[PDB]
Image (tube, coloured by chain):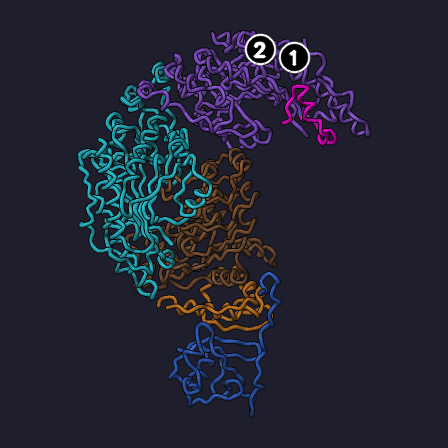
Chain colours: A blue, B orange, C brown, D cyan, E purple
Amino acid sequence: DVFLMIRRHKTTIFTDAKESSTVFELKRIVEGILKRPPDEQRLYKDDQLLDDGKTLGECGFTSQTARPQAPATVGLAFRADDTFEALCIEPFSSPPELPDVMKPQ
Amino acid sequence: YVKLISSDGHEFIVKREHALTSGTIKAMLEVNFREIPSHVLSKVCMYFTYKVRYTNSEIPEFPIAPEIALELLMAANFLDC
Amino acid sequence: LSNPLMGDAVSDWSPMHEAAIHGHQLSLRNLISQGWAVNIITADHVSPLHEACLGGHLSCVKILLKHGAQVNGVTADWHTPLFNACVSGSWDCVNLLLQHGASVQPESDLASPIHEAARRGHVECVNSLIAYGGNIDHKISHLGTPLYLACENQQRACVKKLLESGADVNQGKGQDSPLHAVARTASEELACLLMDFGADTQAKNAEGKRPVELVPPESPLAQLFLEREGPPSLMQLCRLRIRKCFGIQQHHKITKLVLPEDLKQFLLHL
Amino acid sequence: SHNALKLRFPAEDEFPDLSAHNNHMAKVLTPELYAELRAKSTPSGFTLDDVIQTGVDNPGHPYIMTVGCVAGDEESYEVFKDLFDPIIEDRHGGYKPSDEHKTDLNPDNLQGGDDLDPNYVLSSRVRTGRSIRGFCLPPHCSRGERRAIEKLAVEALSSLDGDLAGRYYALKSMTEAEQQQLIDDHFLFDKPVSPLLLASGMARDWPDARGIWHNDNKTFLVWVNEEDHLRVISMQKGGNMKEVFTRFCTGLTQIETLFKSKDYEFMWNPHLGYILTCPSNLGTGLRAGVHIKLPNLGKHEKFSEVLKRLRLQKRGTGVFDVSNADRLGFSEVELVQMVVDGVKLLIEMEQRLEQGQAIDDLMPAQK
Amino acid sequence: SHNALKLRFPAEDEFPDLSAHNNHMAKVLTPELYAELRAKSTPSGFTLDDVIQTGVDNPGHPYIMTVGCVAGDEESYEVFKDLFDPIIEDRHGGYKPSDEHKTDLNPDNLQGGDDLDPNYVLSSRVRTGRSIRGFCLPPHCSRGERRAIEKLAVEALSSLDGDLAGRYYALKSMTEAEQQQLIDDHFLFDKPVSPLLLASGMARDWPDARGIWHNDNKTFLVWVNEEDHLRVISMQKGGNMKEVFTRFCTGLTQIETLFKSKDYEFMWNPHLGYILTCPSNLGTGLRAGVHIKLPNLGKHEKFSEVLKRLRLQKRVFDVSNADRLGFSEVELVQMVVDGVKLLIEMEQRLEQGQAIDDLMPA
C-alpha cells in the first residue's frame, strides 16, 4: 500500500493507494474531493509532472517511502484554462525554539 | 473525508474514519481547530493513519521531533489522544 | 592480629572488629587510644570499617574514617565498605562513605552496590549512588541490570524509582527484558508500571517468546497484555520522547517547561 | 564454689539472655535445659555456665555463625551431653548420636596427589590438635597441670629422630633474636586477642608453660598449650601433598608412641573421635589445604558455588587458601583425599577459564 | 571441686612465677605464704588463685605499679588478710590493720569550697563507690544476684526527688539516640578494655543487668553493676565544690537510707571503711577532682612535688586527691579545696613574673 500526501498552496490531503494503481486513478482520487475532472488536474513529484499512464511504483513511490509513519509528498496544480497553476506549496509553520532544559548537553 | 482547519489556515483532508481516532473528534461527530497550529496539526493527522494501519497486525515506531513534542503533547491532550 | 597464625578464622578477630560489628563506640575509641590502628585487618582483608559498615554503625565509621580507615579497601570476596553499607542499607553511611571518596563503581563485577541495593529494596541508597554518580543501566553479566534485579525480587519501590530516574525499561538480562521477568513472576503491578514506562510487549526472549507467551492465559496479565497490543496513544509517545531529552534524575527540570500543570504532572509521573 | 550461691536462685534468674546472640549454642540452649543442666557438674570441676560462657559473652556475628560454647574435658561431653548432642549434630551436618566415627592416618590410603601442579599449588599444609588423657583442657587447667603437660611434651619432642628432630623454645623466656627468627617463619605465636578465645579463659597465666618446637627443616611445627593442648602443623612449599601427609602421620605416630611409653594417650573414643575443646574440632580435628594461585577463578561468578559442593573452605591471606571443610564422619586420610580431588578439579577449572572456555562441565554434584 | 584437684599438686607446682611482675602483689606473696593459704577459701568459694589472677595476668608497668589483687567479697579481706594486710600497708604509704579508719558525710566540716576562681576552675566532680553487704563483689557474682542488685538499685533510685529525680538507662535496651546523648555528656560507660579489669572476669555477661541512672539536671550518675556495685558520680561546672559535695553527701545518704528501708546496707567496717574490689580503693574510696586551667605552673619544674606535698594527683590538668584511706572524707576534699586555692595563686605568681618561694606546702 501507498500512503500519499498531496498538497496545493495551503491544502493537504491524505490518501491510500496500490503500487499498481496509476496516476490516472490517483487523479480521480483527487476528483472525489476536488470535484473537477482529471484533465483539470496536475499531479506532480517535486517539479516533475506525473504521467497518468505510470503506476505509483513506476513513478518511484513505494512502501519504503510512502509510509503510515510518514507519507510521500506529491503536489497538485490545476488547469487554468490553456495552462496550469504555479507548482507551489506553502510550508507549514516553522518550529519553536527548543527549551534549554530539553536542549542536549 | 473531513476537512480540518489549522490555526494558520491550512486545510487537511482526512479520511473521517482515521479522524475518529481522536476522542474529541468523535465528540464532534468539517472542523476548525483554531487552537492547533499548522506546525503540528499535520503531524496529528499522520498519527491517525499510523494507528489505524497498525491496529490489527509488527508495529513500527512513530517518528517525532523534540521541536514538536511539547506542542504535540498539548494538541493530543486537547484532541483526547 | 599480625600474622598467618594458621588457626581458624574464629581466632583472628581484633577487639575492634568486635566493637565495630556491635556498635561499641566508646570501646572503639578506647582501643584506638591504646593503639589499635584502624587499618588492622584479618584473614580476608577485613577491616573494622568493613564490619562497621555491615552493622550500619554510623558513628563508628565516622570515627574510623576520622582516623584514616580505608574507605575503598577491598576484601578477599571483593567487598568494599560502600558495598557493605549497601548490604545493611544504612543510608547515612552510604552518603558518608561516598563523601569520603568511596567509588560507586567497584573493581570486581561480583559486588555491585547498585545491584545489591536493587535486590534489597534500598531505594534511598539507590538514589544516592546514582546521584553521586552511578550508572543506572549498568549491565553486569549474571545480574543483567539493576532494574532487572528489582523486578526479580518484586521490589516495586525500586522498580518505580529506577524507572522514574530513567532506567532503560527494555534492558534486562540478555534477551530477558524486565517485562519478560514480570510475566515470569506473574506481577500485574509491575506489568502496569513497565508498560507505562515504555516496555516493549513484542520483544522476544532467548527462546523467541514474547512476555505474554511466558505466562498462562488464565492470568490477569493476559488481559493486561491484550490492552497494550495495539499502537500507543500519541500522548504516550510524546511523553516518551520528551522524557528522552532529560538525563538520569534530570527530569526535575520538567517543572521549568512552559506547559500546563496537568501535563507537567503527566510527564513527572511518567 | 560460687556456684553454691547460684543454686540459691531460680533457674530463670540465672538463665542468660541470649536474644541478641547468633550461634549454635544459642539456638540449642533452652530455659528448660538450663534449669536441668545447671544442677550437674563434672568430676573435674565444670558446670553448665562455664560450658556456655563464651557463648553468652559473645553474640558473635549476624552472618558468621560461630559455635558459642566450649568443652572442659573428656567427661564434660557426657555430663553436658544434652547440649552437645544438639550442638554437635547441628554444627557437623546431622552427625547422629550413634554415628560411629573412624580414624586413619595410614598414607597408603591416599591416592594420587603425588605432585600437584606447582603452577598453582604454591604450598601445602596439614594441621591438627590433640589432647592428653588424664588432664583437663586449657579453659580449666591449673598452672601445675599446664606445667606437667609442657614437660611431657618436651620430653617426647626431644626424642624425635630424623627430620622430626628439632628444638624446643620456651615462650616465656625466649630471646628476642629467637623471636625474630620465629616470627619471620610465623612459628612464633602470641597471646590470644580475640574475645571469642579470651572468654574461655585459655589465656590464663600466659605465657606460663607455653612452648614452640620445630624441626631442623622447618616443615614440622608443634605448639604447646595454646588454643588446645598439642597443636601440630606440617608444611612444605610445593605441591607434594602425598609426602606431606605421610610426614604428618609419622609425626603423630612417633609422638603417640612416646606418650604411650609413659602411660599417656590422646583422648579418644568411638563416638566423637579425638576429644578437643571446641565442638567444631571433634572427630579428626584435621585441617588440610593449599595456597592456590587462582586470580581467574577468584573472579568467576560460580567460584564459591563450586567450592560449596567440593566441601572446601575459601580463605584469603595475612590467591586462596583452599582447605578441608569437614571434621567429623570422615576417615582422616579420606578428608585429605577430598582436598586432593577438589584441588585438581579446580586446577582444571582454572585452565578452561584461562582459555575463555565454558567451565560448566566441571561442576559435579558433590555433596 | 577442682580446687581439691589442684591441692593434689605440691605448692611448688601451683606457685606462679612472680619474678616477671612489678606489682604490689608480686612483692608480697611468698611461696611460703602461698603454700599456707592455698587450701584456704571463703564462704563464696573464692581462693588464692582467684585473688591474684589479675596480678599474674598483667606483668605491670616497669615504673608505675599497681596492686593486682581483686577481692571476692568483704569476707575475703579477712580470709586472706595474711596477704592483703601487707599489701594495703604498702599501698597507702603505711597503714597498720589496727589503725581504725574514720568516715564523714557532714559537709559542714568543710571550710570553704564554694569560692574558687572560675578562671581556673573549669569544673569539678566527686566520685566514689559502694557495695551491698550480702552480695559478692562483681568479679565473683553470678547473673542471679547481679540482676537482684540491679533491681534494688533501680527501684530505690526511682524514688529520689527534687534535683535527685531522674531516670534509668538499661544498657541492654538503650537506643542510639540515648547513646549519643550519654556520650556527649560523658555519662555512657562502655565495656572495660583494660587487662587489669578483664583479668578479674568482671566483663562477663556484658551488659546483662548493667545500666546508668541519672538525674534531670545532669549532676548525678549512678553506674549500676559496672566497675563495682554502685559508682556514684557527682559533678558540676564552676568553683562550687561545696554545693556539689553537699548534694553528694546528702544525696548519697538518702539512697543509703533507701536501701536500709529494704534491709540492705553498704559494706563497711572500722578498718577498711567502705568495701570495694581493689585494695587501693579501700577506705573512703573518695575521689574528688577538678579541671584546672594551669598554663604557667604546669610548665614549672616543681609542679609535681607540690601536688605530692598536697596529696594530689597529676592526672589543663585533672587534679584530684591521691589518697583513698588515711583520713576522713571531709578532710580529703578540704585538701582538694585548699590545694586549688594555693595552685591558683602559684600560677598568678608566675603570670606576674614572680617566684613561687613561700607558697611551697609540706
Q: Which mark is residue C2?
A: none
Q: Between residues C1 and A27, which one lies in front from this camera angle?
A: C1
Look at the image and give the residue range highlighted in magenta.
Answer: E291-315
- Return the residue at label 2: E253
Q: Against E275, is C46 above or below?
A: below
Residue E322 in picture, x, y percent from top left? 62, 20
In magenta stretch: residue E294: yes
Q: Residue at x 56, y 49 (%)?
A: C100
Chain designation of label 2: E
Quarter in which the N terminus of chain E is drawn: top left
Residue D141 in picture, x, y percent from top left? 34, 27
Q: Between residues C178 and D80, which one lies in front from this camera angle?
A: D80
Does residue D228 appear to the left or right of C261 in the view shown? left
Which amino acid does the dot numbered 2 rest on?
Answer: Thr
Element carrying mark 1: helix
Residue E110 in sight from this viewpoint: yes
- Residues at marks 1 and 2, CA–CA distance in whole angstroms: 18 Å
Mark 2 is surrounded, within 10 Å at the Cα level, by few (under 14), some (14 to 19) or many (20 or more) other residues, namely few
Residue C182 picture quarter: bottom left
In magenta stretch: residue E247: no
Which amino acid does the dot numbered 1 rest on?
Answer: Glu
Q: Against C134, is B34 above or below?
A: below
- Return the residue at label 1: E331
Residue C56 in picture, x, y percent from top left? 48, 41
Q: Nearer the viewer, mark 1 or mark 2?
A: 1
Chain designation of label 1: E
Quarter in which the C terminus of chain E is drawn: top right
